[PDB]
Image (cartoon, rainbow over all chains, first blue to last red; front, side, top):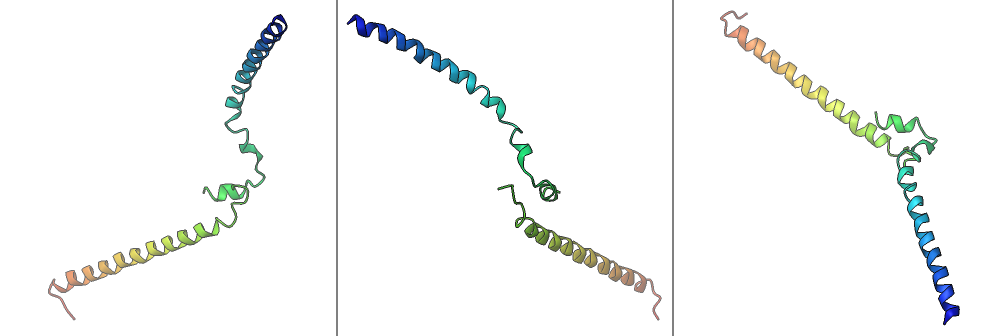
Length: 52
Length: 49
């Protein structure tokens, strides 16, 4: 019993530490959306003749 | 899908050139009706030849 008690508390910090990592990671993704991917196309003359 | 934008452009050049054609036709019907209304005015004055 006290063998498995020590590993259980030692794995509940890692479960809570890996949760905090995703909340900081997917608030950076929420800023990445925008015009990060807009200045990637190398076809700029046809996409201004189409809109005009 | 926005990479090419090539074979989607001349099918808007087509429908835009027909609309500028249909404008110039009906702008010509409103210029021959205004010829009929210049003759019927002058003829019903009383002076024919």
